[PDB]
Image (cartoon, rainbow, N blue to C red):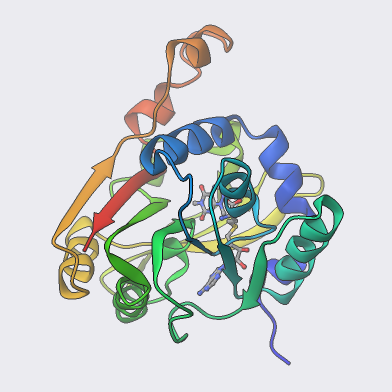
Length: 244
Ligand SMILES: Nc1ncnc2c1ncn2[C@@H]1O[C@H](CSCC[C@H](N)C(=O)O)[C@@H](O)[C@H]1O
Ligand SMILES: Cn1ncnc2c(=O)n(C)c(=O)nc1-2
């Protein structure tokens, strides 16, 4: 038996997704990158309780498979599929160490790569994703912006309190907590843009593109003036699409 970090977070992550200001921007940006899923087979990596895979199934995907390292999160994911009677299937795997489970039209990986604890493990994850993709498929990912700096402002008001920033091999490691009750602590890794693009190339993707989060006028209208300045000038998050 082996502990995963989210085994102690569990239901609090869903609490975070319902209150954090940044979540609506993440969801909007991710589905903008995904586009139409009708008929597609989908692999949702670091699936948590299964949000993205389940919404992708709700938008008309064919087969949807979810993978997460946390037995606790997979247990919550399976209970949601049981409650809504949907066909999602889930597996407990460490993505840096797993075998491919099939060839998919779409791999969705929201908040996977920032949990690679070395550039070596980053590279392994991308290789695994490439081995899971049909030749005309694509990877849609959401991860930490390599250029985020804690000196330029915390993200706590958007839902993620970043507690510190430490050099960690060629990148950085951050301790943090989701703004929940009580707050739920976790750690994540900020690898450089160069290491990401090298991991993508060496895994056999010919195309990648970074995607700035889709913050919109209606988001700005409904918060006090300047609320989104740190989000715009020191963004913690970024989108990423890769194609074989
Ligand atoms: N190496 C790894 N392999 C697979 N899952 C991992 C992982 N490291 C962390 N995770 C999982 O990644 C998740 C981050 S939470 C993100 C959940 C979901 N994608 C959403 O946005 O709704 C946690 O469930 C955690 O257990
Ligand atoms: C899982 N998850 N969900 C939302 N937001 C984040 C996030 O900002 N960071 C930095 C992170 O490591 N993990 C997140």
